[PDB]
Image: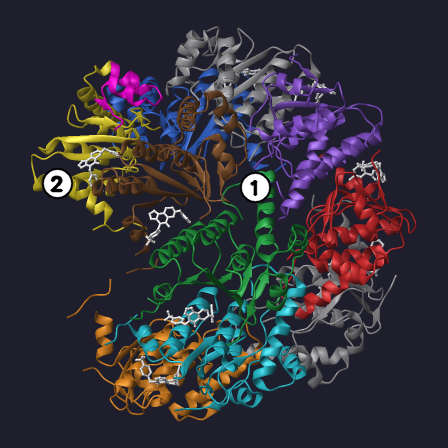
Chain colours: A purple, B red, D cyan, E orange, G blue, H green, I brown, J yellow
Amino acid sequence: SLIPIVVDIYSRLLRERIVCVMGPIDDSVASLVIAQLLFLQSESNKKPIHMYINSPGGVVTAGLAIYDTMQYILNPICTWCVGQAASMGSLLLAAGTPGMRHSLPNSRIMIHQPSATDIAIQAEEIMKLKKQLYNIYAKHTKQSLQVIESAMERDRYMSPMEAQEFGILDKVLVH
Amino acid sequence: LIPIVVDIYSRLLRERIVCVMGPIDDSVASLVIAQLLFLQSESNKKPIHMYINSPGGVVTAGLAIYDTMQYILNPICTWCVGQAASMGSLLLAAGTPGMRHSLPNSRIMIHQPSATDIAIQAEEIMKLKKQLYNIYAKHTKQSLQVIESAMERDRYMSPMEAQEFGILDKVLVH
Amino acid sequence: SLIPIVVDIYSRLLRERIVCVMGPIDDSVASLVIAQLLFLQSESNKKPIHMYINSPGGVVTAGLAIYDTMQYILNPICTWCVGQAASMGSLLLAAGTPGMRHSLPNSRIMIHQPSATDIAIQAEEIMKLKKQLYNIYAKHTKQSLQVIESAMERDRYMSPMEAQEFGILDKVLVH
Amino acid sequence: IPIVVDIYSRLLRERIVCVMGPIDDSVASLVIAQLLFLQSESNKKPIHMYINSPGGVVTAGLAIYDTMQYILNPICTWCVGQAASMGSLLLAAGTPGMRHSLPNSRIMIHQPSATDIAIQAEEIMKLKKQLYNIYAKHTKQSLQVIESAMERDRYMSPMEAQEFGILDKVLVH
Amino acid sequence: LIPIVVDIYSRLLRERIVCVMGPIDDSVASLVIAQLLFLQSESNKKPIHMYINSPGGVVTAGLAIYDTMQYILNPICTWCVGQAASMGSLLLAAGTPGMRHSLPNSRIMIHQPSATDIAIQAEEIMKLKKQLYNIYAKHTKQSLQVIESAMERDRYMSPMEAQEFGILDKVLVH
Amino acid sequence: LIPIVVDIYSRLLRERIVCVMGPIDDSVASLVIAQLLFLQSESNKKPIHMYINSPGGVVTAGLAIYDTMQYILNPICTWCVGQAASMGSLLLAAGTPGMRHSLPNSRIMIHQPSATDIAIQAEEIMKLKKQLYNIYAKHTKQSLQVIESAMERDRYMSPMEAQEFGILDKVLVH
Amino acid sequence: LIPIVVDIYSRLLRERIVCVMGPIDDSVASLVIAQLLFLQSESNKKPIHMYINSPGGVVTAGLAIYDTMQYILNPICTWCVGQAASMGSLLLAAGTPGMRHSLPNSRIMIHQPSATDIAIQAEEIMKLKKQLYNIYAKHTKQSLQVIESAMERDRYMSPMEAQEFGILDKVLVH
Amino acid sequence: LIPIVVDIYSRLLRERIVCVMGPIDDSVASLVIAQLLFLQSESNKKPIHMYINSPGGVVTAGLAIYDTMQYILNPICTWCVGQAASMGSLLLAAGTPGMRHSLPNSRIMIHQPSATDIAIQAEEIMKLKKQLYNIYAKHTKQSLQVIESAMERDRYMSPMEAQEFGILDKVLVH
Amino acid sequence: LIPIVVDIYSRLLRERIVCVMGPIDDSVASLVIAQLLFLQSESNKKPIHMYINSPGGVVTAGLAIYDTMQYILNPICTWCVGQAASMGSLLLAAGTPGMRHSLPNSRIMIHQPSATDIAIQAEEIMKLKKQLYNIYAKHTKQSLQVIESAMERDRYMSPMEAQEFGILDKVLVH
Amino acid sequence: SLIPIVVDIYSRLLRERIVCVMGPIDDSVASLVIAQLLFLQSESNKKPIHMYINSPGGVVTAGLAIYDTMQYILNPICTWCVGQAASMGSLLLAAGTPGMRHSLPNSRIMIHQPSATDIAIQAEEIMKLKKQLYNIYAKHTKQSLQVIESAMERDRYMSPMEAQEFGILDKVLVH
Ligand SMILES: O=c1c2c(n3ccnc3n1Cc1ccc(C(F)(F)F)cc1)CCN(Cc1cccc(Cl)c1)C2
Ligand SMILES: O=c1c2c(n3ccnc3n1Cc1ccc(C(F)(F)F)cc1)CCN(Cc1cccc(Cl)c1)C2
Ligand SMILES: O=c1c2c(n3ccnc3n1Cc1ccc(C(F)(F)F)cc1)CCN(Cc1cccc(Cl)c1)C2
Ligand SMILES: O=c1c2c(n3ccnc3n1Cc1ccc(C(F)(F)F)cc1)CCN(Cc1cccc(Cl)c1)C2
Ligand SMILES: O=c1c2c(n3ccnc3n1Cc1ccc(C(F)(F)F)cc1)CCN(Cc1cccc(Cl)c1)C2
Ligand SMILES: O=c1c2c(n3ccnc3n1Cc1ccc(C(F)(F)F)cc1)CCN(Cc1cccc(Cl)c1)C2
Ligand SMILES: O=c1c2c(n3ccnc3n1Cc1ccc(C(F)(F)F)cc1)CCN(Cc1cccc(Cl)c1)C2
Ligand SMILES: O=c1c2c(n3ccnc3n1Cc1ccc(C(F)(F)F)cc1)CCN(Cc1cccc(Cl)c1)C2
Ligand SMILES: O=c1c2c(n3ccnc3n1Cc1ccc(C(F)(F)F)cc1)CCN(Cc1cccc(Cl)c1)C2
């Protein structure tokens, strides 16, 4: 509700190839984001797609569904963190095309996983998910598994500069 | 809410894309069934694509979709993104042979969770589970014994081991 | 994301002479179903009207309202059971035109009544209603009154092929 | 709850354990404790068990059943009001010749459509088959007739229950 | 709280007064049955008095009390004050002949309101109603036809109309 | 609810007027951010007007709007009507210098109330609090020490006094 | 549930009739303000009519409307129907002098109820009452003392008492 | 609602019969521990009997009871009636060797349900399962592998399967 | 509920055993404080035993117990069974040196979860966090830097590893 | 519940002339505390009474009711702050007999009033209450009104040392 019409603002964002992942991640967000990503690739397999992330995280399998769609599609993907990017949110941020992951000056980044689950699962599977994130995180930051898991073991946010040095993003820009 | 293009969920249907992601209930089954029959009227032979990201749901609602997939003449490509558990993996395994896919980081589970339209007797719950035994055995080409033994474990499968088991055919990445 | 549009899908099903009854049978479902049947008869008193049934049952008087409407209209009525047809659902399925009652391979049929009432009723009327089902069931299955009453007391589901042998449906189709 | 020269504590002084309600784990524990206490008082004096239950958790009912067979005491079961599902199983498990009903009591063996924990289909069936053998044992009915009867969602009269083997005597006073 | 006398509800039991004031449920049934069995153990022949001010309740719980009244050897005086509807009037009518009482302004109803422990079938609810037909006919000395015909009307009866019907015998003022 | 004029909230947007009335959360932030980014596409440097009547809200959502205001090239005139507390006053103070306004009877508060998207540790709440210090110090031209002292007090300030503090520049009447 | 004409509330605003019926909160305030600013853009000189049937509301939101009325150049006729209490009567008294009206049975109360957007200190609520004191004193042209004593009485006023006090100018029936 | 004898649950504890019926939580654990420590103070050598009818519960609370059994010097006879699942079967298997019993129809399950006192990380839940693995392996005398494969199956065991697996020693009926 | 022995929780107190099982709040703090102050009155220097199986709780309530332990003259043996997290581990580490124990399968965590009596500012939460640093550093004999690093990690430690960290001194089995 | 018996611990505290004001202040706490204070004076008008405070504050009129009882009774009153003493709690702490107000090392003290009310009242009365506290606070700390109101205007806790220097208490003791 209370969405203005322009000549619809969220639909007008999509004509600029901008997908929003604001808010928590659940299955409905994942399907909606995925549909827009596949739609944007069908318009052009070569024009860049932009993703604005202001998310506290969400369901792990729903987040991996988006991540896999980003890897699948051919388009370069520029990720933009505004507000914060925590848990799966920071993973999507880190999953952008190298050199095209940006953050605003006062944005917050967190890779620690929250202490999320569609259905009840056992620790053998919940741990498989955590390692699944380890390898994904290690891939895109170019850090060893020892470095990724140790950082994520600590509950703390990073400044946009700090997430750049750890390897989550490439550019902390102001204007 | 849902953005408008050139509505995006109607636009997915415009490409012969049916989504069965999210939990399966009787109304979800009816809606999916309506879309499959509508797509068959467009072309009895052009392929239908079905995206699965479901943790399962009502068994009779899942079988309603399954029987509808088997009924229509169209080839059906199943695509597992996110995860497919319980009835979700059955629909995934029920795709056209050679046309069942998953993305690299997907979770697949055939184990049934401990879902029910009405309270039923124990003989019917066993009659229903036996129905799933035969369906899984049909499309995975595994014996009944290995299927019943497999679902006994409350564990998920990776897309590559699910392929060797016969639930899907290709783990693609682009 | 509740309803897709076709090039409305539930209105398009109605353009195809297909009435679908999935949710549980209540007064609001009955009125809406009845309206479509009278609408489809006004379009053509002779083209077959189709009924897709996937219901766990519902209000008995609301089911009889649909049942009575089926008998009244002149059209041949093809009933199609997908998923399941229990209590009033199976009564509607069995009330189709003879030779036109179908089920899909893995569907469930149950005539046992669950242990259904708009308002509070006395025991005497509940028995009058149960007897009402006996005659409707006995009529359309061509089974004895006794075999119907003993069958319904058993709390079991039956497969489409034993349901065909019982007389509730005629064709278990395979495509 | 009235005091007498406590009324439920006084019933236990008369070797009467009352169920009279759904079979919880808490009901089962309390009933089981009373049976073990009454046996320790006397392994040979009969214990009376009053049943007015619509059933309950199956594992909790089997817990009581296992305790009844364990103790050496003759057990007189008395069904007043009604005895459905697990309730009728306890009724039929009394000592032979000592299972009674009041004239207007209700007996039901049909199982309701054991939810301590959510369970699988294979285990749920293993559980009813476990109930079949107990009923088959104590009614002296074949396994086939027991399973067919339980599939019918009907109540029995105290005479229908006496002839079926669930009880032995329908008395008025 | 309950006042203390030198406890008032326990003092009523010392006077062979059982209270059935309030709706009938299984927990009420256990207490009434327990007190009746206790009072019989004190004396097989001294009369027990039963105070009824109930709007009815669970049918199986009411019949459980009814069966206990018939079982014990004691004469039972039923006293209806306030009102006695559904099972309340059945217990009232089930007193010893010549000892069923009402106060001038009590309400009596045999009509059943529109058995309630668990969901049951149509044949069982009808079997339960037929049991009520025979019991009422036994203690009112009316034919079955007049019992059911009367019960179809939910009118309440005056303690006088109920006496002529056979539900009670002595409606007193002092 | 909302009137149509030859829609009133969309018509405010046609006049380059963004409204931040009400509490700030992530959904408010997304909408404000979208309108700010949209308004830049019509004109690189035409001024944008921002109406604030907010009691505050989520800090990360407030910083998200703040960063967007600083990012875009347009000069931004902020207008406080009613009140601007917590993050509300930060957005008000973050307008283009010389263009931060209040109406005569508005209340302004920079003290933060005792809020976050998720539960966080003590070190992060302090980092955010320090982040607010630096932003406030930057735009008020006050030292860090005086800013910290101002926020320590649970008091509101009048528009004409917020001007002397540096939160706004002009308190207008007509 | 709103009837449509050549929308009835949009047709009212189409004639410069702003409605403040119902309680004041921030969502009401934003809408009233937008309508006042919109009506000024069509004509800074055509009179605006404002209908008040409000029991009061949030004080900061009421002051926002008050500030918007004072800011715009239009003459504003306020019309009280039903009642105007707390902030409602403040908006009523804030109309253009000589253009404040009431209907015969409308009720006026200046007493403030015993709220605000957020929990605040005792000094801030007191700053607000003195702030309201001056507003009332300005437009009723009574001394500050007369306002404080009047608002202190938990009573409603008749439209004749309201004009004599200085809150309004005309009570018309036709 | 607990009957009194010369309290029935206090009379059970008076004979060294500790009951673990019902789900395990911290409040149950404290009480069981206190009873075990109390029974040891009367005699470090008289056997303690422990009745288990539990569907499981909090793992840390279950381990606290397990640690208390191992600490005290008394031989402990565990008795399974009804069922012993999750932590319940762990306490059952943790009895003194040769003194672990079950009744004929009691059910045993080692599969862990898909909780804990507080929300925790994936590594900590995994530390707990390996920790339970060693406990089960110790007292059933099966390899760690055999425990992990067994607990992986979402199935209950019969008392005969339970003794053969090493969880208990005797299934008695009399 | 609670057994009587010739009351079990009062009998633990007769043995100078205070139990801190369950979460800590002000009502828990008052009761523990009262028992600690009471136990000092029987004996100035007889050791007091403290059983901890707590996931933490209110920080000011936890410090209230901590200050009482430090205040009283008695040596205090702390015993961790089950788990001791957040304030729970602080009380465990606050025992008399050489007398802080854990049972083999206990879990210990000093990281604080992301709690307070009333809503507070960022400066106070940090002062309390720093207060916890100094207490932890004092009793573990670790530097402030290593303590802050330990608490930053959302992990539990085993009893034998908490010993090397200095939280406890002896992990006992019998 | 779960209160141990000693040979009752809260009743045994009262035989040691120790009143507990732990938890929030409401009318029921005030009456209960007041009754114990009057009882302790009736036992001895000259033996000291001890008050343990671990309170986040509460209803202002209920707190003033306790304060007035402390001033009325003749006994010396030793106040002890453990945990924290906020809003009205710190007022009761400050109201002890001079030289007999103590705190434990890690206790928290706050005079700022929370942002509490039996019934809805106007600002003229709510402000009268605040000034009523100003004069009470100024009395027992011996600070000017300007100093009291300015300190209380700032939202912050004090360390037990800091509350001593401001004048709330006299002794920060450890053993
Ligand atoms: O300003 C951009 C930016 C991008 N971008 C990509 C393609 N076009 C653009 N434009 C132009 C444009 C946007 C929206 C619309 C319309 F839809 F609202 F009309 C019309 C034109 C990329 C990233 N971003 C950076 C950014 C700044 C502030 C907050 C956030 Cl979260 C991120 C700016
Ligand atoms: O990209 C596809 C894919 C399919 N497919 C089938 C027909 N057309 C397509 N296109 C083009 C297209 C899609 C959507 C729209 C519109 F509706 F959004 F506009 C318009 C054109 C099938 C398989 N799939 C694979 C896939 C990769 C990543 C995640 C997921 Cl869940 C699945 C891609
Ligand atoms: O496919 C059919 C079937 C019937 N039928 C009757 C008339 N037309 C049809 N069509 C073609 C068609 C359907 C819908 C549309 C549109 F409206 F959606 F566009 C357009 C064309 C009846 C038999 N069976 C029914 C059925 C029910 C439930 C589960 C399954 Cl597996 C099978 C299929
Ligand atoms: O069929 C009728 C009936 C009446 N009637 C009156 C005028 N025209 C009609 N038609 C034709 C028609 C119906 C609906 C539509 C349209 F809504 F779909 F457009 C268009 C034409 C009343 C008499 N009878 C009543 C009736 C029988 C069975 C069950 C129910 Cl419940 C009620 C039916
Ligand atoms: O019968 C026992 C059994 C044990 N046992 C141990 C010590 N004494 C006994 N007695 C005698 C006794 C019990 C209770 C009391 C009193 F306190 F209630 F009065 C007095 C004497 C061990 C367990 N075993 C097996 C068992 C059977 C049925 C259900 C359960 Cl769950 C377990 C029975
Ligand atoms: O009447 C009995 C009956 C038994 N029995 C066994 C031992 N003593 C008895 N007495 C005497 C007595 C009862 C109660 C107390 C006191 F404790 F409540 F005061 C004291 C003495 C067995 C069961 N039988 C059958 C029965 C008939 C009616 C309804 C129910 Cl439900 C069951 C009755
Ligand atoms: O009056 C303005 C003011 C601004 N401004 C900026 C651009 N245009 C304007 N106008 C004209 C206009 C408004 C609304 C519409 C329409 F959309 F409703 F039609 C069309 C034209 C800025 C600041 N503001 C100050 C202000 C005073 C009172 C209350 C509030 Cl909340 C704020 C006035
Ligand atoms: O066994 C102890 C232990 C202590 N201790 C201290 C003083 N006395 C004892 N006893 C004897 C005793 C206990 C209870 C009672 C009574 F109250 F229940 F009767 C009477 C005597 C200290 C530590 N603890 C260690 C411990 C092991 C297992 C689980 C837990 Cl939670 C803790 C053992
Ligand atoms: O230890 C005291 C202390 C006082 N005091 C006053 C009179 N007697 C005492 N004793 C002896 C005693 C207390 C309780 C009982 C009994 F009731 F529990 F049995 C029996 C004897 C005053 C203040 N206080 C300081 C204090 C330390 C720890 C926490 C807190 Cl909140 C405050 C200690």
Using the image as rendered, state which of residue B167 and residue I105 is in the foreground.
I105
> Which chain letter matches label 2?
J
Front in this rendered view, residue D82 or H86: H86
Where is the C terminus of chain D found, in terms of image quarters?
bottom left
Task: Tell me: D70 left or right of A73.
Answer: left
The magenta region covers J147-175
Q: Amino acid at mark 1?
A: Ile
Is residue D173 depicted above or below I163 in this figure?
below
Q: Are marks 1 and 2 on the same chain?
A: no
**Residue G174 is at least partly visible in this image:** no
Q: Which residue is mark 1?
A: G2
Task: Tell me how far mark 1 sits from mark 2, CA to CA.
Answer: 69 Å
Q: Position of residue I16 (x, y in %)?
A: 29, 46
Query: Is residue I2 in view?
Result: yes
**Secondary structure beneath label 2:** helix
Relative to D170, B151 lies left or right:
right
- Ligand 5 falls in which quarter? bottom left
1 vs 2, front mark:
2
